[PDB]
Image (cartoon, rainbow over all chains, first blue to last red; front, side, top):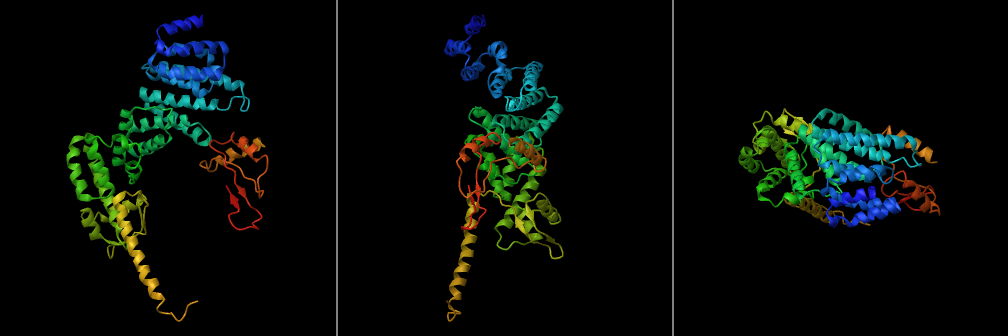
Length: 388
Length: 68
């Protein structure tokens, strides 16, 4: 009796988790499928404590893949296989269920009940790729994710859960490959799409904030840090002093204080080996940010090469390499006149601004208020004889 | 015609994929009874809250011929 067999599934269960079993019973009795989904869905959530859930799934819920949301059913294989260190077993169940949906879809049509089976399929494939990243085998990770990405971006309407899985994996992949740019972007998307039904560890969120900070520090094309310093995840790691130097570092960086940063790196540069490598980057990136700011504040935007040299403490030959590279990343637009050694700087990129940097804007705007004060108030007097 | 929709849509997606189907519009200067009924239909082909705006084609009034 899969009812009573189910009751020896209940023998090893914490009886505190038992009261749902009766539900299952009557539900297996009444076969109100939505109610079952509720029941063994939340149950199963808490029965993550129980490997039993496998056979639970593997018995009648295996019978029951016909019933409920495919996101519902697939969540089960997810949390079930989560612990599993047998990867071929995971992939096994995965392509198994897949084949079952190839059947269901083969029979059924769009408005006829097979529409978002595609969704379950996609989600599956996502976690499959995850399994590979766990399996290493890192290439089929890549091609599976990439093949998935098209199918995604053509579908306009898809549940969020899938998307959180997709960026969830891509994050990991780039994290192995150590492409920092791509990692960073994928991350921020992942976070933005994160949902309450996804409960993730505070230790995790701390970590993710850390690796994200590093990425943006070592990222070639990442020059805007306002995203993270104001991003709600940084509030998790903010208070730990073991990391306080880190905010000293980014905070120092977006306000582009050359010397102070240059002090900061001296300590931690010995500490974190990943920082030991890529010191070159950090240096370039500083020179840039410094440049950007010294332009951004300046009333009329032009520079000699000397000015940049002293501001960035860069000998002036490179100064034109520094400017040209500042443009090719999109940070600046403008031109260089060597003959006179000027830099015109058409315009400078809008970038999220912290507190202190605002104040100067307040200033310049007070000036450009005053000029108008005097001009307008000065033009009635003259030509007072002409008004209407 | 939903077949006209799901036939055209993906024929847009082949062009600029980043423009996603949102909602519909009727240029009729004021609402109709079935409006609230059919928006419920468009909830099939989009995700969040299908947006219905009304373009004023007569222009005879003042500006903002749209209303969202």
